Image (cartoon, coloured by chain):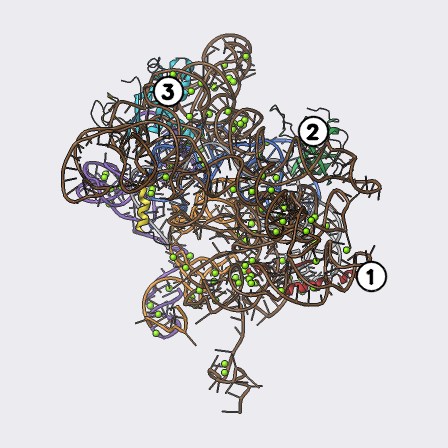
Chain colours: A yellow, B red, C cyan, D green, E orange, F purple, G blue, I brown
Amino acid sequence: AVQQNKPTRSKRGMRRSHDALTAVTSLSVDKTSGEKHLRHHITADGYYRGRKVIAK
Amino acid sequence: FRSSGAGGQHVNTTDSAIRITHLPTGIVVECQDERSQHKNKAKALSVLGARIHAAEMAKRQQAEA
Amino acid sequence: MRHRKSGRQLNRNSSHRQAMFRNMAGSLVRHEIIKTTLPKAKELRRVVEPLITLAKTDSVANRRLAFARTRDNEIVAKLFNELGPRFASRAGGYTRILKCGFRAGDNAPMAYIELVDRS
Amino acid sequence: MIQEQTMLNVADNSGARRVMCIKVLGGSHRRYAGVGDIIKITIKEAIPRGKVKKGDVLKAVVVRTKKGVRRPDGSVIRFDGNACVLLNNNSEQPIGTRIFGPVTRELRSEKFMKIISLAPEVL
RNA sequence: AGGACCGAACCGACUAAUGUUGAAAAAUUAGCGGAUGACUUGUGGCUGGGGGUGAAAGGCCAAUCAAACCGGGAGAUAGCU
RNA sequence: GCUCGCCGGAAGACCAAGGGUUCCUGUCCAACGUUAAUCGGGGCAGGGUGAGUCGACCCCUAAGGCGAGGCCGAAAGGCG
RNA sequence: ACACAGGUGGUCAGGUAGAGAAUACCAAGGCGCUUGAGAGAACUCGGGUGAAGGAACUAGGCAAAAUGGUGCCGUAACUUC
RNA sequence: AAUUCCUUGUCGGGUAAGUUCCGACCUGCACGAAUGGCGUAAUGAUGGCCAGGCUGUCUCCACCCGAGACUCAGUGAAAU
RNA sequence: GCUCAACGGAUAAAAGGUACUCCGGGGAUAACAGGCUGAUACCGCCCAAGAGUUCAUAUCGACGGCGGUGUUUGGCACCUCGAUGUCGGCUCAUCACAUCCUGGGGCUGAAGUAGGUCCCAAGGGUAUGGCUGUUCGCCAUUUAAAGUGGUACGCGAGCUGGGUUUAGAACGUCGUGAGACAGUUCGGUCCCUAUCUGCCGUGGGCGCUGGAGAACUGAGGGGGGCUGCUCCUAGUACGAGAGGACCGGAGUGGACGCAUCACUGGUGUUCGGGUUGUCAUGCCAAUGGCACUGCCCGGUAGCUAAAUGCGGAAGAGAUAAGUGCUGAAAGCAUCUAAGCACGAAACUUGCCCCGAGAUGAGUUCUCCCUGACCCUUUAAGGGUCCUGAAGGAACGUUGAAGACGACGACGUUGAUAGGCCGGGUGUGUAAGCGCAGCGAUGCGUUGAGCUAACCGGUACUAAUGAACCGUGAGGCUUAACCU
Ligand SMILES: [Mg+2]
Ligand SMILES: [Mg+2]
Ligand SMILES: [Mg+2]
Ligand SMILES: [Mg+2]
Ligand SMILES: [Mg+2]
Ligand SMILES: [Mg+2]
Ligand SMILES: [Mg+2]
Ligand SMILES: [Mg+2]
Ligand SMILES: [Mg+2]
Ligand SMILES: [Mg+2]
Ligand SMILES: [Mg+2]
Ligand SMILES: [Mg+2]
Ligand SMILES: [Mg+2]
Ligand SMILES: [Mg+2]
Ligand SMILES: [Mg+2]
Ligand SMILES: [Mg+2]
Ligand SMILES: [Mg+2]
Ligand SMILES: [Mg+2]
Ligand SMILES: [Mg+2]
Ligand SMILES: [Mg+2]
Ligand SMILES: [Mg+2]
Ligand SMILES: [Mg+2]
Ligand SMILES: [Mg+2]
Ligand SMILES: [Mg+2]
Ligand SMILES: [Mg+2]
Ligand SMILES: [Mg+2]
Ligand SMILES: [Mg+2]
Ligand SMILES: [Mg+2]
Ligand SMILES: [Mg+2]
Ligand SMILES: [Mg+2]
Ligand SMILES: [Mg+2]
Ligand SMILES: [Mg+2]
Ligand SMILES: [Mg+2]
Ligand SMILES: [Mg+2]
Ligand SMILES: [Mg+2]
Ligand SMILES: [Mg+2]
Ligand SMILES: [Mg+2]
Ligand SMILES: [Mg+2]
Ligand SMILES: [Mg+2]
Ligand SMILES: [Mg+2]
Ligand SMILES: [Mg+2]
Ligand SMILES: [Mg+2]
Ligand SMILES: [Mg+2]
Ligand SMILES: [Mg+2]
Ligand SMILES: [Mg+2]
Ligand SMILES: [Mg+2]
Ligand SMILES: [Mg+2]
Ligand SMILES: [Mg+2]
Ligand SMILES: [Mg+2]
Ligand SMILES: [Mg+2]
Ligand SMILES: [Mg+2]
Ligand SMILES: [Mg+2]
Ligand SMILES: [Mg+2]
Ligand SMILES: [Mg+2]
Ligand SMILES: [Mg+2]
Ligand SMILES: [Mg+2]
Ligand SMILES: [Mg+2]
Ligand SMILES: [Mg+2]
Ligand SMILES: [Mg+2]
Ligand SMILES: [Mg+2]
Ligand SMILES: [Mg+2]
Ligand SMILES: [Mg+2]
Ligand SMILES: [Mg+2]
Ligand SMILES: [Mg+2]
Ligand SMILES: [Mg+2]
Ligand SMILES: [Mg+2]
Ligand SMILES: [Mg+2]
Ligand SMILES: [Mg+2]
Ligand SMILES: [Mg+2]
Ligand SMILES: [Mg+2]
Ligand SMILES: [Mg+2]
Ligand SMILES: [Mg+2]
Ligand SMILES: [Mg+2]
Ligand SMILES: [Mg+2]
Ligand SMILES: [Mg+2]
Ligand SMILES: [Mg+2]
Ligand SMILES: [Mg+2]
Ligand SMILES: [Mg+2]
Ligand SMILES: [Mg+2]
Ligand SMILES: [Mg+2]
Ligand SMILES: [Mg+2]
Ligand SMILES: [Mg+2]
Ligand SMILES: [Mg+2]
Ligand SMILES: [Mg+2]
Ligand SMILES: [Mg+2]
Ligand SMILES: [Mg+2]
Ligand SMILES: [Mg+2]
Ligand SMILES: [Mg+2]
Ligand SMILES: [Mg+2]
Ligand SMILES: [Mg+2]
Ligand SMILES: [Mg+2]
Ligand SMILES: [Mg+2]
Ligand SMILES: [Mg+2]
Ligand SMILES: [Mg+2]
Ligand SMILES: [Mg+2]
Ligand SMILES: [Mg+2]
Ligand SMILES: [Mg+2]
Ligand SMILES: [Mg+2]
Ligand SMILES: [Mg+2]
Ligand SMILES: [Mg+2]
Ligand SMILES: [Mg+2]
Ligand SMILES: [Mg+2]
């Protein structure tokens, strides 16, 4: 249920090969407010695809 | 076959128990007394000879009387 | 396996999901826009929008049905007075889902579910 | 769907009321018996004087099951009780002379022609 | 009337599953036995280690008991590791 | 704030034990809180406990403890 | 040892159904148990239902299932009555 | 036989089939009379056996509901 | 002046128990397993006295002889006593052939049927129960058969804990006693989140020599491989009869496997209803909450088995034992030495699945990019600007796809999901009102209302204008060509 030897910092770094984060690829710029948001999300000031979908 | 009872592991692995099945008659014996089957086979062949000569001398004392 | 199945479970037993979606449909009717997670908002559409299709016929029966779905007289008196003739001509799709980012407390995908004819 | 340890009712005047299936004949590893399947049974309850005695071991043929039989159209004939008609072990022909209750069309053959020719209702 | 019957609190722990770096150095859950008595419980008091106490299992005596705990003799001795 | 759910011979209210400022208010978020925290039984600062009748003290004794003298025991002490 | 599924003596005892302080839903009153959000694989844990058969399971009917209340009729060997 | 080595004694019953069980037998290895014998109604979370109902125990597993698992965000052990 | 005799004499003077146990140590030394050996065991073989009416070798085979296996009981004490955790069952297996079944044969004291024994053959198959903790065994009924063994007498970091093998108790027996017993009997804690190898799945990374999308050949690997009963040939061959076939053909079964949900069903806490208790909605009415979904009754989709479809084969090649043909060596004989033919569930194909990471990285079809410069250390060199293709990926709507990834459908030129509309289906005559009834209720409106996942439709909602990645004609040497 346990190791018999100490795994090296080589085997430890190899396991963390796939722990790397995937950075955001596209930040769509809103066409009216001109502020950046996530593609298919509303902005931080309540715009989405031009119109003001929700007030602040 | 393995013996069955107390005594521990040494019972539990070694067979040391011999059953002998006499084919043309059908008298069987199951001696299990020692811890070695060689003392348990000859002291089981000693019993069948004492249970076949005890089976014709019993047969020659029914059709005698 | 959930082949051809439908309905979310939301880590909740049956008598809680029916109560929570009642407390939530009775709040989307009152304020016309609420803020909730995105998996809870895609399953409230399946609750609220049959209560506005139930609102397109102002009978004594449908008042008594829509009080069995909401148990709130103020909601039923908004569904049939106000939201009834508001969506009297839309063929479904009475609501709108607006993804609004991620919550600070548990990183949940939040969303705004709102009514269509609101502003 | 008769298996072993199954109490069956009796569908003739052979002299038993209640028998128990102790083997399903007709193949190694064979689980169940439909109708028209030869099973070996023992007699758990008999009338005080009849052709068979309590504790006898003899064959039977299953005439009625509660799981029923499916006809080729998809239709199925389910009864309310498992039944059987006792046989002889060697000749393998029925013992009683007056079959009780209905039987089905799956029982008639060159083997069990006598049983369907003695039963009241052949569904 | 009752070391009477059924059964909650109350006291106990018969089976099973869980748990076994647990929620817990012995418990939980569902069933279980006593439940006016040789019952249970509170607060105080007494019995001290070869001694106590024991409806008696070598049981209990502060998670410790075929002889407690802490201080000393004491850096016991160890043909053994 | 509006709903919803839970317990209700308790998961309510109030004593004694025990704890010892945890109570209350203003303030603060490093640590502490099994996450975060503007919140806390956490940090800092101030406040709060009012009795002829309640409880203790007091008066009375139970077990049991101490024990003038006394009896006993190498000494310590033991019993009374 | 912890903001620990344990343990801690006494007092108060409402409604409806019920014999009851069982128990269900409630009141007064107090809480939602201090990580959440999704997903709806194996597998495990705790539960629900089951065709035909009904102890073939197994060391063993273990576990589950079932029986369950009141009033009345009725009730065997045996017995220390 | 809570006791019997040979022993699954033998015979009967029970079961399709019974090293257990119950009834006899007596050849009691090695019972036996207050380290008590033989009975014994009631009682037993007592040991063994049979029958009835009942059933996922099983044939032979299916499906479902919740809590884990699983992914994401936060915190973050252990034996070795 | 000591049998101090345990005789170089521990003292003149010395028995036991521990399963309540404890410590120091040992694999220096036992029980388990491994190992070495093979006495024994098991299996072959050699001689053939005999048995077999006569006839050693159809079948057994005395007296003796030689080996094999490691397989029983042992022997030795080499590995482990700073732990190698144990019998039986369960669950998975896996190999061996010394074959239980099925297959192919030789001999038979083989009429046939059916046996006998030997040889070849490991492909698949190789019961359920009663008793017992049982392995083992006996028994019941089956079966084509209920194989023998190896794998720590396979398998407890998978399960069980009956037996043994602790502490309690009792009996018999032994002991004066503590206690004892390969004697029984009642009771008695089985722990571990997987680092590595392993294995089952499934991804990411790069490689495959320009990039990308598809379709592929198949080096190889895996799966699969069971078999009865009836009928026909034919009551013919055979036989005094009784009995009863070879070969070949047909049906229909069992167990197993793969698939699927149309059927019969199962579930269906997301559908409909009945109902009890209580609380609430101002009350009646109607509903709702909670009581395991409160208890039930049904039940759509899905998933499923008990449901119903298919599967094993046939063939072919080469064969094993075997049967031969021609045929010498050896004027004959002879299956072999040359040459040739048949010959099995075995072997190779045939059948389904995986499969170019097959680095030996393959083949075919399609698509896409045809800019400028410099720099020095001229090289598969480095930089700048311009450029950004095919395509991919992200995001979103999602799925009869899925743990996550992946896979698939879809993104307004849109049916991808929800909704909506229509139907289907399920529940079984909704509420409100009217009447009949003293009332509970019944009747009518009304097969009504409600109806999840289904089916067919419909842009109503959400699937954005984009942006990001990936680029600029792809090395060298020969060779065949090309004008
Ligand atoms: Mg090591
Ligand atoms: Mg990782
Ligand atoms: Mg012993
Ligand atoms: Mg051994
Ligand atoms: Mg769907
Ligand atoms: Mg969760
Ligand atoms: Mg509920
Ligand atoms: Mg009493
Ligand atoms: Mg006690
Ligand atoms: Mg309990
Ligand atoms: Mg009682
Ligand atoms: Mg203690
Ligand atoms: Mg002491
Ligand atoms: Mg001492
Ligand atoms: Mg000293
Ligand atoms: Mg020292
Ligand atoms: Mg409640
Ligand atoms: Mg309280
Ligand atoms: Mg403080
Ligand atoms: Mg406070
Ligand atoms: Mg404060
Ligand atoms: Mg902070
Ligand atoms: Mg914090
Ligand atoms: Mg404070
Ligand atoms: Mg006073
Ligand atoms: Mg006094
Ligand atoms: Mg004095
Ligand atoms: Mg005194
Ligand atoms: Mg806490
Ligand atoms: Mg009450
Ligand atoms: Mg209660
Ligand atoms: Mg689940
Ligand atoms: Mg159901
Ligand atoms: Mg059930
Ligand atoms: Mg069933
Ligand atoms: Mg049924
Ligand atoms: Mg059994
Ligand atoms: Mg069994
Ligand atoms: Mg039970
Ligand atoms: Mg129950
Ligand atoms: Mg008998
Ligand atoms: Mg007797
Ligand atoms: Mg005796
Ligand atoms: Mg005695
Ligand atoms: Mg006497
Ligand atoms: Mg005596
Ligand atoms: Mg006595
Ligand atoms: Mg008692
Ligand atoms: Mg039985
Ligand atoms: Mg000496
Ligand atoms: Mg000497
Ligand atoms: Mg003792
Ligand atoms: Mg030791
Ligand atoms: Mg050694
Ligand atoms: Mg050994
Ligand atoms: Mg050897
Ligand atoms: Mg030898
Ligand atoms: Mg001859
Ligand atoms: Mg020979
Ligand atoms: Mg010889
Ligand atoms: Mg070996
Ligand atoms: Mg050996
Ligand atoms: Mg070793
Ligand atoms: Mg060792
Ligand atoms: Mg070690
Ligand atoms: Mg061979
Ligand atoms: Mg032959
Ligand atoms: Mg095989
Ligand atoms: Mg069996
Ligand atoms: Mg048994
Ligand atoms: Mg084996
Ligand atoms: Mg061996
Ligand atoms: Mg083993
Ligand atoms: Mg094992
Ligand atoms: Mg045991
Ligand atoms: Mg003992
Ligand atoms: Mg990959
Ligand atoms: Mg292959
Ligand atoms: Mg179907
Ligand atoms: Mg369908
Ligand atoms: Mg159905
Ligand atoms: Mg279905
Ligand atoms: Mg109600
Ligand atoms: Mg009402
Ligand atoms: Mg409530
Ligand atoms: Mg149903
Ligand atoms: Mg072939
Ligand atoms: Mg050939
Ligand atoms: Mg040949
Ligand atoms: Mg010739
Ligand atoms: Mg010639
Ligand atoms: Mg075949
Ligand atoms: Mg082959
Ligand atoms: Mg269209
Ligand atoms: Mg749609
Ligand atoms: Mg319909
Ligand atoms: Mg009508
Ligand atoms: Mg209704
Ligand atoms: Mg009506
Ligand atoms: Mg309908
Ligand atoms: Mg509809
Ligand atoms: Mg559609």
Query: On the image, which quarter does residue G77 sit in?
Result: top right
Q: CA distance from mark 2 to mark 3?
A: 60 Å
- Badge 1 marks a residue whose secondary structure is helix
Query: On the image, which quarter does residue F15 sit in?
Result: top left
- Chain ID, mark 1: B
Q: Residue at x 33, y 45 (%)?
A: A15
Circles 2 and 3: CB atoms closer than 8 Å: no
Residue at mark 2: D107
Q: Nearer the viewer, mark 2 or mark 3?
A: 2
- Chain ID, mark 2: D
Q: Where residue D58 sits in the image (x, y, percent)?
A: 73, 39
Q: Could you say which disc has been placed on residue B61 in the image? A: 1
- The answer to whether residue D51 is visible is no
- The answer to whether residue C48 is visible is yes
Relative vertical location of residue E76 with respect to residue B46 in this rendering, above or below: below
Q: Is the CB of mark 2 within 8 Å of ligand 36? A: no
* Amino acid type, callout 2: Leu
Q: Where residue I83 sits in the image (x, y, percent)?
A: 44, 59
Q: Is the CB of mark 1 within 8 Å of ligand 41? A: no
- The residue carrying pointer 1 sits among few (fewer than 14), some (14 to 19) or many (20 or more) residues within 10 Å by Cα, namely few
Q: CA distance from mark 1 to mark 3?
A: 105 Å
Circles 2 and 1: CB atoms closer than 8 Å: no
Of residues I126 and I220, the one nearer the viewer is I220
Of residues E41 and F62, the one nearer the viewer is E41
Of residues I69 and A11, the one nearer the viewer is I69
Q: Could you say which disc has been placed on residue C49 in the image? A: 3
Q: Nearer the viewer, mark 2 or mark 1?
A: 2
